[PDB]
Length: 9
Length: 248
Ligand SMILES: NC(=[NH2+])c1cc2c(I)cccc2s1
Image 1 (cartoon, chains in turn green, yellow):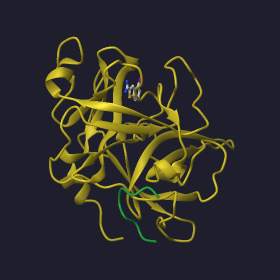
Image 2 (tube, rainbow over the protein chains, first blue to last red):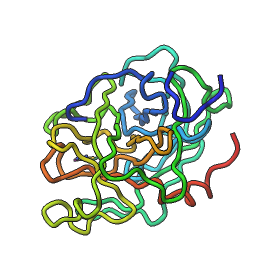
Image 3 (tube, each protein chain N blue to C red):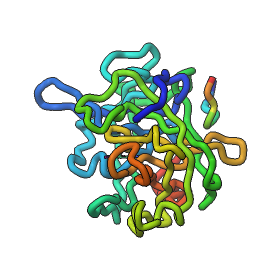
Image 4 (cartoon, chains in turn orange, purple):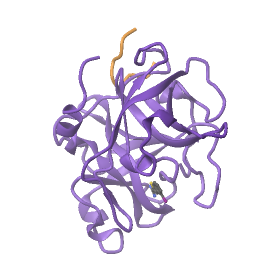
């Protein structure tokens, strides 16, 4: 959606 | 990366692949990098030092292979190439080895969030994990120091951070390692970063977040006993990063 630093999905 | 496993970008969605174009028709890989914010990638100065002509580099995000496309990949041009003033190289170490690349798409945009493109976090002022922390490095660098080609699939491995006291021991690197560097190795010197992995990330978890703790910078040989990989200590360059980055 938007950038969430450090998140892998 | 010597040792390691092969991975896909879903596992390192902030990894950026930097290539250079040749007046001949070929694009070759140069170094790796990491996405900090929508328009900025951080890498290492020594990757550009010899040819600081921004217009000849191309940056790809969402890339799991080296010379074949990955669906979801984004291509950018380098709008700005910032190298470190005070960058120096001696017979081993590189000092102040950090560079910033502002990217622009052919449509005038920066990176967009996807399942293969994400930003990595920055540490807070001089804040690092303790030695012993296991961090992971990723990249398309050599799998053996004697190879002359790079793998086509992205690889990752886990290394542990070591203290300066250990790395500055005479039989390691002496005073070539400074307080603005960090050293990481495998207890049993089995896996490590190598040539072609320069500029890529050393990610560790700090206070809950996956943080960019270091940038692959140098090493003597690859996966050599008592010859750790040395990385740029990001937590020490925060002012410098700040004075050059802005907005979204
Ligand atoms: N041992 C290492 N971790 C490294 C070795 C090198 C070499 I040899 C060249 C460029 C970057 C790196 S990192």
